Image (cartoon, helix red, strand yellow):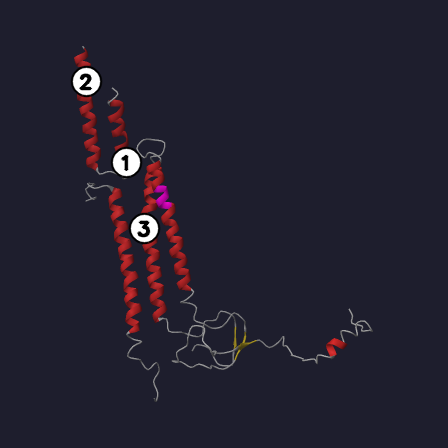
Amino acid sequence: QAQKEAIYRQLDQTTQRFNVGLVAITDVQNARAQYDTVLANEVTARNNLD
Amino acid sequence: LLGTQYISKQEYDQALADAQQANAAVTAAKAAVETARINLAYTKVTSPISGRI
Amino acid sequence: RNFKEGSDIEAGVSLYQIDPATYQATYDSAKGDLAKAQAAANIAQLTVNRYQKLLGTQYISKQEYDQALADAQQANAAVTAAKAAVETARINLAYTKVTSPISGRIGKSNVTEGALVQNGQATALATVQQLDPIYVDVTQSSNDMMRLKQELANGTLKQE
């Protein structure tokens, strides 16, 4: 969850770079995939918790 | 490559900076030829009017 | 030549045509480099406009913004170099010639069309003159304008 405060924050600015124009659409759809891997690790963290 | 938005919009304009400034450099060199072409209208000394010499 | 000889010509009335061929080139080298400075500062103006929207929020990391706010303020200064370098080479282009900024009656044309003229040449092209307030160089003797100034002690008297 400190990675999801980080890599979503990475997504929440690579998206806000594309809304300006600094990155290509790959670096959004990459950074979402690097964000959604954080979910598929953090959900397993919440699953390996239980 | 930005019709399908596949490079940055920034790297385009930065290349469009380089496009427009280098075409602004050719104009700054086509004039520099036009400086030195006009020396070769200043050699071969053109009679600036007509009439008798 | 573009006036009528002996007429009356106002100030700034460009009626000599020095050959622009060299100076139209130096105007185009300079107005080229204005666009070489503008279009290099145009995108330097976008890269602040594209980074101003990320200030306080996340990526732009104020120094990497202020490295672009260098490059906008620095390359807009390069425009101010080149826009004045145009304004230098504009006042060597539309700087041909007539008249010198007096307004009055033009005399001859000591030059004629085709004769090469030089930068601050020895002779003159034409002489614009203004006539209605006119001077007369009265030329007093020296011993008088001691004596007539020493007649301020004995006399004079000049008034009012």
**Are the residues tagged 2 and 1 within 8 Å (C-beta)?**
no
Q: CA distance from mark 1 to mark 3?
A: 22 Å
Label 2: which secondary element: helix
Residue at 32% in and 59% down: C32
Q: Look at the numbered disc 3 and give the secondary structure of its residue.
A: helix
**In which quarter of the view is residue C157 placed?**
bottom right
Q: Are marks 2 and 3 on the same chain?
A: no
Magenta stretch in the rendered image = C68-72
Badge 3 local density, few (<14 within 10 Å), some, or many (20+)? many
Does residue A48 show up magenta in the picture? no
- The residue to which callout 2 is attached is A43
Give the residue at mark 3: C40
- SS of the residue under disc 1: helix
Q: Is residue C159 above or below residue C79?
A: below
- From the viewer's perspective, is C7 left or right of C38? right
Residue appearing at x 33%, y 46% in the figure: C44
Tell which of B38 and A20 is nearer to you. Answer: B38
| Residues at marks 2 and 1, CA–CA distance in whole angstroms | 27 Å
- The reply to whether callout 2 and callout 3 are in contact (CB within 8 Å) is no
- Front position among marks 2 and 3: 3
Q: Chain of mark 1?
A: A
Mark before the other along the chain sequence, 2 or 1: 1
* Above-or-below relation of A43 to C39: above
Look at label 2 and name its amino acid: Val
Quarter-of-image position of residue C134: bottom right
Mark 1 lies on residue: A17
Query: Can you give x and y, in whole percent of width and height, for residue C12 in the image?
Result: 49, 69
Residue B39, relative to residue A28: is it above or below?
below
Q: Is residue C88 left or right of residue C130?
A: left
Residue C70 sits inside the magenta stretch = yes
Chain of the residue under label 2: A
